[PDB]
Image (spheres, rainbow, N blue to C red):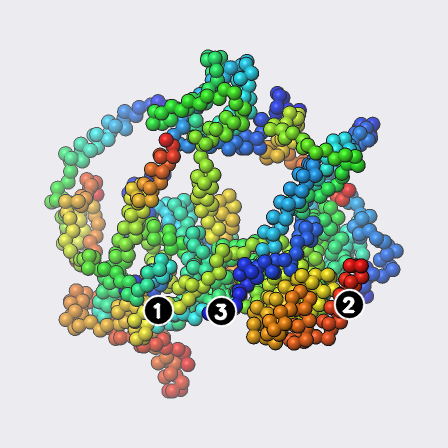
Amino acid sequence: ETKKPTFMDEEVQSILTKMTGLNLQKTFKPAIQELKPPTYKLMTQAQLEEATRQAVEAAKVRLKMPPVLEERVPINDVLAEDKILEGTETTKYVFTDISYSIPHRERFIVVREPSGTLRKASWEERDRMIQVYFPKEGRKILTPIIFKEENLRTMYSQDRHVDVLNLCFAQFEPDSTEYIKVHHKTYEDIDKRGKYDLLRSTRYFGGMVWYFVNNKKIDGLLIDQIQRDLIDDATNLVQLYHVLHPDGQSAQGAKDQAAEGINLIKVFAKTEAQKGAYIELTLQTYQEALSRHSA
Amino acid sequence: PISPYKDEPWKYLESEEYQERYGSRPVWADYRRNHKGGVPPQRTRKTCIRRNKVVGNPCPICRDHKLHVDFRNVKLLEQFVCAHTGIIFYAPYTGVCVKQHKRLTQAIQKARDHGLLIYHIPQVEPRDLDFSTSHGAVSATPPAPTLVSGDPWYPWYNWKQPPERELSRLRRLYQGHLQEESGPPPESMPKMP
Amino acid sequence: PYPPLLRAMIIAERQKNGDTSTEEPMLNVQRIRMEPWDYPAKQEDKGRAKGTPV
Amino acid sequence: RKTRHDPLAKSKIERVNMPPAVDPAEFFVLMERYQHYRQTVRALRMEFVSEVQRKVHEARAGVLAERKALKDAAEHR
Amino acid sequence: LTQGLFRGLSRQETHQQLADKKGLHVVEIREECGPLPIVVASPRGPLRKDPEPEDEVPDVKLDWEDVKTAQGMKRSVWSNLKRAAT
Amino acid sequence: KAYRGGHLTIRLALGGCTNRPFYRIVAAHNKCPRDGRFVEQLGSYDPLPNSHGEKLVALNLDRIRHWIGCGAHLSKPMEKLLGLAGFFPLHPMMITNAERLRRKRAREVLLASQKTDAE
Amino acid sequence: PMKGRFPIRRTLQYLSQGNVVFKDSVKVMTVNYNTHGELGEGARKFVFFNIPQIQYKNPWVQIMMFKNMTPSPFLRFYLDSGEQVLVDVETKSNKEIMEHIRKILGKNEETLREEEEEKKQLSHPANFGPRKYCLRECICEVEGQVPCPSLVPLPKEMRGKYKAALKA
Amino acid sequence: KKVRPRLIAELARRVRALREQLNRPRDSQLYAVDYETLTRPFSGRRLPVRAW
Ligand code: FES
Ligand SMILES: [Zn+2]
């Protein structure tokens, strides 16, 4: 019938890509790591334009937004129950098929409990064993202590939200509960303190827009874009909101009035936006300043 | 010597007694080792304090009892880390003893675990190419018949009492070397009350 | 029947390849003719004691 | 360990290892378990043996393999 | 040693002189900053429209000491030693 | 090296330090030393429980099925690891050793009960 | 400095830049070039720069050179089946020659990646052993597992010295 | 690479194999048994207790 666009649709990818923008200075910020003496080349105006172009192609590969998944379902499956083995052992065995040419989500990992029950390993146990025999740089077997409440607040206080997302992407899987909680908590702190610029020109901006839209918290973001002369992104945010929520006061009103450009913000501001008054004032200031420049 | 900054060591670096002694340079700047030759030993002394007794030329950490190596004193731990590569200097670089260089590396790694010290965190790639849990390994498997009826996987797991004619053969086969016949085992494992 | 794990890995290949079936995988033990341990062996392939009288 | 030429000890000269006692019930039940267990494993072994024979013959004499050997020879000409 | 040190440190060509000499952009490539081209110097005069002819093999005299190190062949128990700060 | 006769076997190769054993599953010739030369490594076994209280066992099933199809044998401890996993059936003596333990513990409950009852 | 003209040729970084990896058919490569003549200029540069690159990638291939035997230069390959591949290289640069033999007798990029991929499967990360072959030697290097006794002494209840004493 | 011949290693090998065929023990010597000590006098080995 009518399916609502997903996070990986070409239409949504292009919208979230444009909002993110491209900033080479922040995308390729000098890393604090082991250094080497740089290399120099004598280039022309055209050779410099091509090199700057190849950096744009490589930055769009570094800004690739990770896919957004739903919380994976627990694993509760028993392969066999051998009651004769009950009481013969004190601890449980964890068998792990280790074959190189197998994806880790198709890999068999079972557990023989002391009750003789041969079940499948839980998600927490699968991801742990896959790191013992197929280690990955950045991931640790034991959950770090940085992802705790008190420690995460410290990182937020230093405006290191992109660091928390990079730690979470290297330690947890996209469909894990911790990957979702840590991401969602970070998104809620930005909206509270208006730090939307931090995630700009990164691969974590789209996922942040996708969370506010589905939970209807685009008021703060929509304001920031207006305060930065980014109306094109501000209008695309309302267009996206209407798509995912067709049966909304703003969506229905827009169709009736056929609002376009700045009008969409006004229609959405009064009907559905919680901070309708503040938006109109902010949008008002911008439109006045824009008129002066046009003169 | 009882330092007043024992519990709050970060207050000594932001005081005037620290500025009048070190200034803006690190604590290990005006320190030189006493060794024979131009090339120094590749290891520093184990410790500058032996049974509450300090050596003639203590290291930058052992000479000032008000400098406490804690994971909270971020301003002191930054003097032992390169601001361009984020690498901890080896002891011969600064001149600290092995005992304090082992305490700094821990405190420096404990502050990076609490988010107090800034360090480079790369942007890694995903572990898996696909994210589909459409496989038996991660999903439910059709319970086998024997599992639904509460039966063992193979019939010969359970005890089966053999005929009498077969025991007589064994008794005849092993005459004078026998053991008391054992009956069917209990259904479940006993426990000590 | 196949043992627990092997059975679970044969049913997953079916579903991965697309074949949909509810039949149980089972081992054909009819070929395996288990003979008793006291069955006469071959004496024409058996060795002999060496000539080292003690 | 010892060799054939090394002699025997004087403490093992008058030694007789008596066989263990037999439980008629357990002995018979356990004598059938090995009979089935070993029959179930003899079939598994034959299965795996057929898979190693297949792949080898497939590799040197297969459809895909012979479909690529002709493509490489046709591209050479 | 001293008369030669001051001699080579005074006859070194900067990035600005090089650009003016060849009328081309001097771009800096760093591994830490990825493929981003950093312009360190540009000519004040007319920028040339033709590029430098790419050379298949450069006829530049090498130093066996540097080539022997890059190939993991210069063994020495005195190099890369831990020393004090300088 | 060439051994007279012999065959390939999938056994356990002890490792680790004193009071800290760590076995590594390997396919090696029958006459070769325990911890000597091997053909391939097919897994590992850590007897000592970890922090989570679980014993880890790695198995390269794809390769264990290859060597069993090439003429390789199995050792008793290794046949008991494949039965605990579900790859092989429960070894007959894994079952009988459990029955012996049951009768043994039921024989101790009597004496314990009699003492508390009689005395 | 390094002796000889164009010393960069005698470097591992330059010898590994060759992109001509012959197939299994190629067994012998014979080069016939003239020392003089404008037409044979490229053949001389091909013997001065690239033959080192070709022989380094194909060490089991015999390469024999002949001077001033014919009025014009040419290449000739001898395959294992008995077939000969004549290649006139007159009025051509060394790059055209290096690119031409790569198309008729050299392997493509698809055939190379495959071979490399096979090697990656020879070093299983799960395996434990010496640093030369494996990443980890023992499983005590894995956090969570019991550490080595050399670093962290084991509990008195887990040592065979006291297990025997406690029992007797 | 020219191995130096070992002729005595081949001479004795032939002699041993020959003597094993001319001095071979018979079934009367090999499989004899003393019914009091229950030992084969040829090798002086006791039979298993279950065969006595
Ligand atoms: S090396 Fe792993 S236990 Fe000693
Ligand atoms: Zn000290």
Vertical arrangement, residue C28 with respect to residue B184, above or below: above
- Distance (Cα) linking label 2 and label 3: 39 Å
Q: Check disc 1 and report the residue beneath it.
A: B142
**Residue at 22% in and 67% down:** D28
Let me know if residue A169 appears in the view: yes
The three-letter amino acid code for the residue at tag 3 is Thr
Does C32 appear above or below D25?
above
Residue A31, percent from left and from top: 68, 50
Outermost bottom residue: F118
* Amino acid type indicated by mark 1: Pro
Q: Which residue is mark 3?
A: A2
Q: Residue A224 is drawn in which quadrant?
A: bottom right
Q: Is residue F63 left or right of residue A153?
A: left
F28 or E50: nearer the viewer: E50
Q: Which residue is mark 2?
A: A285
Crowding around mark 2 (Cα neighbors within 10 Å: few <14, some 14 to 19, many 20+) is few
